[PDB]
Image (spheres, coloured by chain):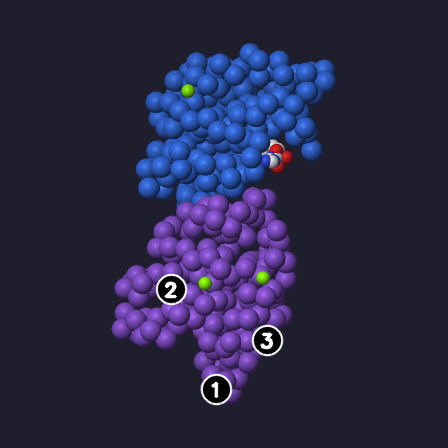
Chain colours: A purple, B blue
């Protein structure tokens, strides 16, 4: 089945990468709501926040979500896409949601902050769980997660 | 590990397609020996054949096989690669060999050294060369599956990237 697949998780969990790798395996399209926002508005999140604050950033993010959602597409979402209940509902409704979970220690170690990742997870862990259909060990290699997800979700390859 | 992985099997078995997906999944370089040969000589098979026939192309193919067999590389090989003993000895003694198996029917459906009905040729090719694929192969996998599944299977049976 071809419902949109939303990858959620905190900063450092490998959403874009795994998201892009899963899309390839399934023959889907791939879109990252942070990247889309940047390359369509011209603005960074610091640009958006400085001009309209976190509330205007959050609104714009919700709008991106609705804009990019479509079948045969994997969507990587920003880390705080799960703060707004309306966003959490939209994802379970339109598609299937996958949470890439990694403990703060390991989220911190990913740098291509451990106290900040710890507090992000105190706030959001529960929202990640609430919104997810499937939860997968994000500390594996991307290819391995793609494989595990095709098995768990029962998705055929391209 | 890091030793060259050789993809073998007959025309239509997916060596290039599956090889690139495997490379990509491992973060490894991919090479195809037919493409390597093209670019380092400038001659298409046809140019080579014209001058030195098929025995010539085989000679240059053997050479290329030895040129491209390096670490963290997935090497896709031409069909005929396994006819020579030297090529078989080389591959097992420098890397790990994967045989992408598929039935002749299926190899002929993929159409999208010729002779007669595609299907009948491929049947005969496979009937004689199957012992050769099996001999050289370390691992054998069902190439009728889609590429990303073949990759997943191969990563589990080969214990990669582990
Ligand atoms: N696992 C597969 N499942 C379905 N089709 C495949 C698979 N692998 C390859 N194909 C298709 O089969 C044909 C064989 O392509 P190719 O990769 O060049 O094979 P080979 O290098 O063995 O000649 C192509 O049309 C390719 O797109
Ligand atoms: Mg749904
Ligand atoms: Mg849940
Ligand atoms: Mg080929
Ligand atoms: Mg064998």
The residue sitting at 27% across, 73% down in the picture is: A115
Q: Mark 1 points at which residue?
A: A53
Q: How crowded is mark 1: few (under 14 residues within 10 Å), some or many (20 or more)?
A: few
- Chain name for mark 2: A
Horizontally, residue B53 falls left or right of residue B8, namely right
Which sits earlier in the primary sequence, circle 2 or circle 3? Answer: 2
Answer yes or no: disc 2 within 8 Å of ligand 3.
no
- Labels 1 and 3 positioned on one and the same chain: yes
Residue A29: x percent and y percent?
60, 56
- Labels 2 and 3 positioned on one and the same chain: yes
Assign a secondary structure to mark 2: loop
Instruction: Please indicate, yes or no, whether residue B36 appears anywhere in the rendered image.
Output: no
- Chain name for mark 3: A
Assign a secondary structure to mark 1: helix
Q: Is B29 situated above or below B119?
A: below
The residue sitting at 44% across, 35% down in the picture is: B154
Badges 1 and 3: C-beta atoms under 8 Å apart? no
Task: Measure the alpha-carbon separation of dots 2 and 1.
Answer: 23 Å
Which sits earlier in the primary sequence, circle 2 or circle 1? Answer: 2
In the picture, the disc for residue A12 is 2
Q: Mark 3 points at which residue?
A: A63
Pick the front one: A7 or B127: A7
- Chain name for mark 1: A
Assign a secondary structure to mark 3: helix
Q: Is A125 situated above or below A150?
A: below
């Amino acid at each position: 089945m071809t419902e949109p697949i939303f990858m959620v998780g905190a900063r450092g969990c490998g959403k874009t990468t795994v998201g892009r790798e899963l899309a390839r395996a399934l023959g889907y399209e791939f879109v990252d709501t942070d990247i889309f926002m940047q390359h369509t508005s011209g603005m960074t999140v610091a640009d958006v926040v400085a001009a309209e604050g976190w509330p205007g950033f959050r609104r714009r993010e919700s709008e991106a979500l609705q804009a990019v959602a479509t079948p045969n597409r994997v969507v990587a979402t920003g880390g705080g896409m799960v703060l707004l209940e309306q966003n959490r509902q939209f994802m379970r409704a339109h598609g299937t949601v996958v949470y890439l979970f990694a403990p703060a220690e390991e989220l911190a170690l990913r740098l291509q902050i451990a106290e900040e990742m710890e507090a992000v997870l105190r706030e959001r862990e529960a929202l990640y769980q609430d919104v997810a259909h499937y939860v997968v060990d994000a500390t594996q290699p991307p290819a391995a997660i793609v494989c595990e997800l095709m098995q768990t979700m029962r998705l055929p390859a391209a």
